[PDB]
Image (spheres, coloured by chain):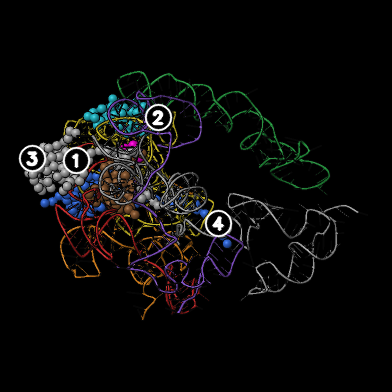
Chain colours: A blue, C brown, D cyan, F purple, G red, I orange, J green, K yellow
Amino acid sequence: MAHKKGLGSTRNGRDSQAKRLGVKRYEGQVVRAGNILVRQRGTRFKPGKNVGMGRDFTLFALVDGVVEFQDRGRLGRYVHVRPLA
Amino acid sequence: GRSTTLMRLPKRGMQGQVPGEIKRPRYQGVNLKDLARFEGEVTPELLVRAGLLKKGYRLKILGEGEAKPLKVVAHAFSKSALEKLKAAGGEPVLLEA
Amino acid sequence: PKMKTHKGAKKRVKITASGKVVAMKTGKRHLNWQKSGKEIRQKGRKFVLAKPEAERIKLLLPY
Amino acid sequence: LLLECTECKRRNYATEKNKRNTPNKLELRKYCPWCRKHTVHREV
RNA sequence: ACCUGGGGAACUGAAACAUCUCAGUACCCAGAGGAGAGGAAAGAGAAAUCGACUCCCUGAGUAGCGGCGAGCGAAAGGGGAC
RNA sequence: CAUGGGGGAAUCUGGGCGGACCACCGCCUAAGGCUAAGUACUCCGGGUGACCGAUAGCGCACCAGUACCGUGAGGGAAAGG
RNA sequence: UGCCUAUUGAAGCAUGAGCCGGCGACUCACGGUCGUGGGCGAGCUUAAGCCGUUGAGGCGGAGGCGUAGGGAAACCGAGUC
RNA sequence: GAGGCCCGAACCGGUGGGGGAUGCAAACCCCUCGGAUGAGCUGGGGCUAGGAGUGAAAAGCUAACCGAGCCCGGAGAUAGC
RNA sequence: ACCAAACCCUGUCAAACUCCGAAGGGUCCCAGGUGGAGCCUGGGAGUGAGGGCGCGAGCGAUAACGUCCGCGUCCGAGCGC
RNA sequence: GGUAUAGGGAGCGACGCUUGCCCGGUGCCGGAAGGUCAAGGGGAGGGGUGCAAGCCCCGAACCGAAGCCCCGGUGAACGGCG
RNA sequence: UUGACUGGGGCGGUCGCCUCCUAAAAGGUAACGGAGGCGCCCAAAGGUCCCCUCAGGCGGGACGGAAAUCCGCCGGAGAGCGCAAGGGUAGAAGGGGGCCUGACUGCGAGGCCUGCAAGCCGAGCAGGGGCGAAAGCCGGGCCUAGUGAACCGGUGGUCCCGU
């Protein structure tokens, strides 16, 4: 045989399933009301013009329009929808 | 060897007691848009033997189209079906025997 | 010989007209899951995509 | 505890959840019934 | 061979298995005969109803039965033979 | 509807049934028996076949349930011109 | 660097085959679903059986699909829940 | 003149070795061994059977492969190989 | 005597550190692009045993024709030239 | 066609010298008390119906075996012996 | 009848969910690879209106450690945010107070994710409410874990069925 005697202190097999987050609708994309725009951990992207978020910080459009992003540094990064004609 | 989809719950309630089905009066439906197809005196039997029914039991008219005047016997009509031919037609109905 | 209809399937699914298979919502069946969450509300009927093609074939006669 | 609120002198339930030992007992509070609009709904 | 009665399996299926299934089948036994069985209502079941029994076609894979699983599955009524 | 065990009636002011149980409404007469036909089968006789044609068709077209095998139950050929 | 098979990978020192000749494996029944060739079309169609035929076909509407769907059901109805 | 006494034929058996290994033989031959008045050997006639028999007991024997005989049947068992 | 807290320099290190941050990748818009391209519905599948090489990482020992993933490719099916 | 000097089961295995301690757990034996306990007895009380008498249904106390719990013995009983 | 995974099997360890990393700057991504949690908890730890802003460091102060409580400067977040980690956050999601009970009923456009079936977000309309003068906010909790198809029954309720 020439056998051994291995074992496992394995106390690490583990992990949660991916939750797929991020900017789901980048800037410039025409969107209908309700389209969640961003899935975020915290408030990585603050809600802007015509954009609301719920319990899990999920930001979504409030009207029909184009998506526009914006940096405000000390203020933060915002995402909003500008309607049209 | 998983679960099929015998996973979905049987909502279909009120289903099968034991002696069996319950002998209850069935009502075959027929629109008058398929009725005006002819004229005169339209009543059960006169149907079945043609068009719809066939011992289908109770004859309840109703429907779209626009039936013309001609006393039409039946077992039931719609709050619509009535008014619809109320313009000119018949109110034959029920039974007492 | 004369395929027999699959009772169980019949007991839990109503097939509409245009050929859609529709059944209830798993999850709420008298909770057993328990203490609400306004979720209980969202339980009407539903369309079983792709799995009805199979569902259906089990009711060949009963239609 | 799996609690529910029985509108006094009728039916309906709210299906709440108290904490017993943790100051409880005598749970009841203005909820909306299906049999017309509000009452208070007790425990049980 | 077919038939009636008395007894009466398992393999298999359920992608394990015990209820269930196969199946009252295989087989064993008694008995009947050119057939055997059944047969003149303490019936059926909703029809002001029908009118011995048996056989076929429907009814119907319906009604139902079922670890409501796998799977099993009528009867009335309607056509016929007699 | 049958029936092994226990209890155990009544004779038409009787008794059973219509899916627990009552009450209505209605059906039928239990605890004795016989009864043709239409139905089933194919040892047997005949007639047909988008049936086989001797490694097929029956296991046997021939002296086959034979020879041979097996204690036995039983298994079981070949071979036509 | 044979043939077949099985393989990530075979001439392969992996499987099978001595050679030849015969026998030798996706069928039929009933349901069902698409496609297709036809008949008929708001209609279509017969079962069992009776009548003829003796390799004549008729007859037979019980029944079955389809003409309305929603709803657990009552029920309603181009609506319905 | 006693004896599950001794040596040793017949008779019963099968210790060790060689040979045999498509055998003379589906357990044999040669040499060598154990028992040999006993719980002995042997003829003839009878009885016990398949989850059963028989067994000084090895799961041994039950018609030349027994941790469940053989034959026929369920039967074309089932085979994710 | 830095044995030695913080603290300031001089030097540095880090998959689970980041003040910073490429190439690149993803998507939307406008264009190009007639391709065994696409998209919608439906009938039939097989496959669900991969393997090598290159590049990027785990495990290993900066071992393995080792082992797991990721992008690509070829073999598989091009053991044809 | 026998009758405890006999039969059955078990273990050890001529003969000699011997065969210690442990009944907590298991088994077996013994315990006319208690505990628990199934049919069945019993009917407090309630329900379905009818106009009713009634016909039907559930059903508490309590009375109820073996078994088990409980009390105790037991090692050539299973076993154990820092 | 006596499970599977498994650098043969047994033994050992493990089996669902959450969070970092591996993961190669969209997602997603393996290994018996590295490293930790969950199977609950809040009747206030929930609504809304109105207020307040931390941790530290440095002095100064009766009892008083090296932070008990005070006063004074400095200190943009290193505290806090019920429990793991992460993201987020004081221009509050943190600390306190007053009234409250939307931890509602009917619904649900439009999406996220995705084989299925599940999971997640959600504006808006109706009804009848809360807090605020108001604009307004309110279908539980800073957010991601705290969970289990069907079948079979149990308690209620009710427009239904009831041979």
Both on one chain, marks 1 and 4?
no
The residue labelled by disc 3 is B89
Marks 1 and 2: in contact by CB < 8 Å? Answer: no
User: What's the residue type where badge 2 is placed?
Assistant: Asn
Q: Which of marks 4 and 3 is in front?
A: 3
| Labelled disc at residue A5 | 4
Residue at horizontal 17 percent and vertical 41 percent from the top: B59
Proximity of marks 2 and 4: CB atoms separated by less than 8 Å: no
User: Which is more foreground, mark 1 or mark 4?
Assistant: 1
Query: Spatial distance from mark 2 to mark 1, Cα to Cα?
Result: 65 Å
Label 1 and label 3: CA atoms lie apart by: 19 Å
Question: Marks 3 and 4: in contact by CB < 8 Å?
Answer: no
Q: Give the Cα distance between marks 2 and 4.
A: 53 Å
In primary-sequence order, the first of circles 1 and 3 is: 1
**Residue D32 point in image, percent of width and height:** 25, 31
Q: Nearer the viewer, residue B72 or D22?
A: B72
User: Magenta residues?
Assistant: C33-38
Q: Is residue C42 visible?
A: no
Does the segment drawn in magenta span residue A59? no
Q: In the rendered structure, the residue with mark 4 lies on which chain? A: A
Using the image, tell me which numbered label, if any, was put on residue D21: 2
Q: Distance between the residues labelled 2 and 3?
A: 76 Å
Q: Please state the horizontal and vertical placement of residue K44, each as a whole percent of the image.
A: 33, 31
Q: Which amino acid does label 1 sit on?
A: Arg
Query: In this image, K94 relative to B87: left or right?
Result: right
**Camera-side residue: K79 or I34?**
I34
Dot 3: chain letter: B
Q: Which chain carries label 1?
A: B
Assign a secondary structure to mark 1. strand
Which residue bears the numbered disc 1?
Answer: B58
